[PDB]
Image (spheres, helix red, strand yellow):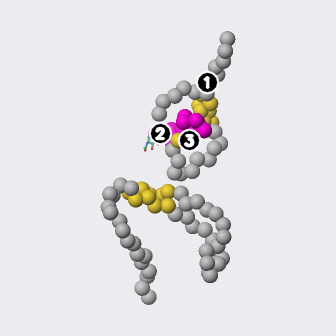
Amino acid sequence: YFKIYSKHTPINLVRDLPQGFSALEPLVDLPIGINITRFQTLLALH
Amino acid sequence: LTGTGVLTESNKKFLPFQQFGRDIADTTDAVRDPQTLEILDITPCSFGGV
Ligand SMILES: *[C@@H]1O[C@H](CO)[C@@H](O)[C@H](O)[C@H]1NC(C)=O
């Protein structure tokens, strides 16, 4: 099961990650059964 | 999910991702209905010694 959780929150600290607590709720759960070992992000080329 | 109890209106704001709630004991406290998607509170039926 590939479980996806996410949350959007305002932030005001670019040197590190702001201090506080927030739990992320599940949104999608895909029963793919794929052996996943690596991932990468995609940025918009400009 | 089966049981016996009184189903009444409730004001517990279930979040979009939870479907049923359980007590400190492994039993249902409230449930979300199918077909109409609503939140029913479950209060145990009255009982007692005679
Ligand atoms: C079941 O019927 C009700 C009656 O209109 C409808 O609102 C509901 O969407 C139906 N269930 C599903 C899963 O669509």
Chain letter of disc 1 in the image:
B
The local crowd at label 1, few if under 14, some if 14 to 19, many if 20 or more residues have their Cα within 10 Å, is few
Q: Is residue B19 visible?
A: yes
Q: Position of residue B26 (x, y in %)?
A: 54, 36
Of pointers 3 and 2, the one earlier in the residue sequence: 3
How far apart are the alpha carbons under marks 2 and 1?
23 Å
Q: Which mark is residue B34?
A: 2
Ligand 1 contact, mark 3 (Cβ < 8 Å): no
Does mark 2's beta carbon lie closer than 8 Å to ligand 1?
Answer: yes
Looking at mark 1, is its residue's CB closer than 8 Å to ligand 1? no
Identity, as a three-letter code, of the amino acid under mark 2: Pro
B28 vs A3, left or right, is: right
Q: Which mark is residue B45?
A: 1
Residue bearing the label numbered 3: B21
**Residue most extreme to the bottom:** A46
Question: What residue sits 60% from the left and 38% below the top?
Answer: B24
Q: Amino acid at mark 3?
A: Gly
Question: Are the numbered discs 3 and 1 placed on the same chain, yes or no?
Answer: yes
The magenta stretch is: B21-38
Magenta stretch contains residue B20: no
Is A28 located above or below residue A10 in the figure?
Answer: above
Magenta residues, dominant SS class: loop
* B42 over B14 or under it: above or below: above
Hey, which quadrant is residue A3 in on the image? bottom left
Q: Are marks 3 and 2 on the same chain?
A: yes
Circle 3 sits in a helix, a strand or a loop, which is it? strand
Q: Quadrant of ligand 1?
A: top left
Q: Could you tell me if the residues under marks 3 and 2 are in contact, i.e. CB atoms within 8 Å?
A: no
Residue type, numbered disc 1: Cys
